[PDB]
Amino acid sequence: VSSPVSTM
Amino acid sequence: IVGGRRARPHAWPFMVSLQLRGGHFCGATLIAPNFVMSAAHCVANVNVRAVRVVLGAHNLSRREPTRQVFAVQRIFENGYDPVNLLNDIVILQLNGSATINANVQVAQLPAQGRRLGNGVQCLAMGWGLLGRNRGIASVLQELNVTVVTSLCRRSNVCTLVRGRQAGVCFGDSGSPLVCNGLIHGIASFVRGGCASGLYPDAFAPVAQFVNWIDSIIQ
Ligand SMILES: *[C@@H]1O[C@H](CO[C@@H]2O[C@@H](C)[C@@H](O)[C@@H](O)[C@@H]2O)[C@@H](O[C@@H]2O[C@H](CO)[C@@H](O[C@@H]3O[C@H](CO)[C@@H](O)[C@H](O)[C@@H]3O)[C@H](O)[C@H]2NC(C)=O)[C@H](O)[C@H]1NC(C)=O
Ligand SMILES: *[C@@H]1O[C@H](CO[C@@H]2O[C@@H](C)[C@@H](O)[C@@H](O)[C@@H]2O)[C@@H](O)[C@H](O)[C@H]1NC(C)=O
Image (cartoon, rainbow over all chains, first blue to last red; front, side):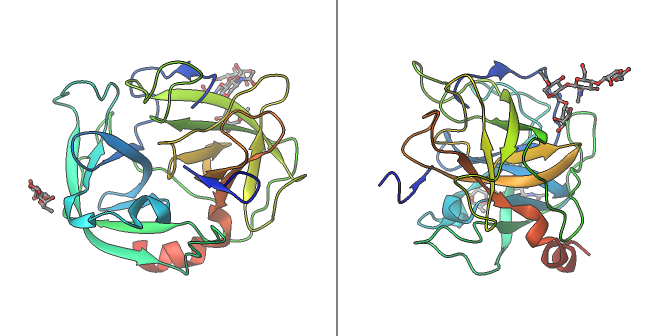
């Protein structure tokens, strides 16, 4: 998921 | 950190490496001799029993006798929202107390309610992915950053570097955001990609939880 979130 | 510079040897003696096997997976911040502050998803699906809290480090590609490894005693969370990535803060109690050397020092936090506006110059760090090419960073990395309010939530503090594709990437989560010698952010998540240049990098908003941190650290 990108614009939803990309937790590192 | 993508697009950043190597740090000076132990210039930031509060910089912590959370390691699982022998490899880095998240960074952290020493807020007390026996306490560590990081990101909640860094311990979400991991056996915290097995995490070694490496402190006073520089190049994690070999052993440094100045490094002090610790283990997690108690895990505190104030309502981590694993899906919305809200309140991505965790306080890890230490096993023991660290020797406040020149290589290991206690970082400090701001007061509860302190909001930084857009334009404030901050500094990010972490042992995360080294940039475009080359993977996890062997040597702690630095990056000058500036706070942004656009394309962000006050449930976060956000950071963008304007004029280059740079910012935090995988493995930097839980690492601090230093703003005027104060820890204002905890690396939570990126949007679209690490150094995207369009979406601001999101930090966990330390200032919203200080009263909670002080109830554990005092
Ligand atoms: C990138 O960030 C580093 C780190 O210092 C930062 O300073 C603030 C602007 C905030 O962003 C803080 O969050 C952060 O700690 C900058 O290094 C700093 O450089 C300045 C100027 O070179 C130093 O200030 C000087 O201090 C001396 C005494 O030490 C005075 O005599 C000078 O007049 C001047 O005020 C500052 O000490 C130094 N900080 C550290 C920790 O070394 C760096 O400049 C910055 N880069 C850019 C392009 O802004
Ligand atoms: C901290 O704890 C260390 C124990 O080592 C680790 O312990 C558990 C939690 C597992 O992660 C295990 O695989 C590790 O071996 C000690 O080495 C260290 O001395 C302790 N700290 C103090 C101050 O005694």
